[PDB]
Length: 13
Image 1 (cartoon, rainbow, N blue to C red):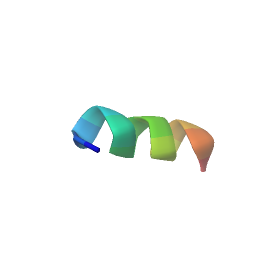
Image 2: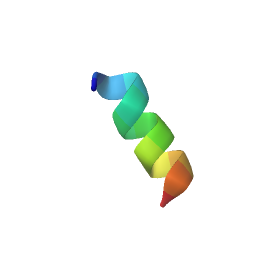
Image 3: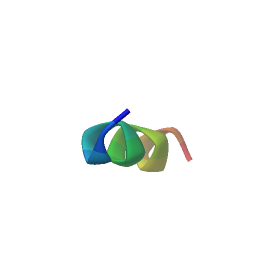
């Protein structure tokens, strides 16, 4: 749940 996950969430979004 790091910034990469946020980037993945950004990728998800």
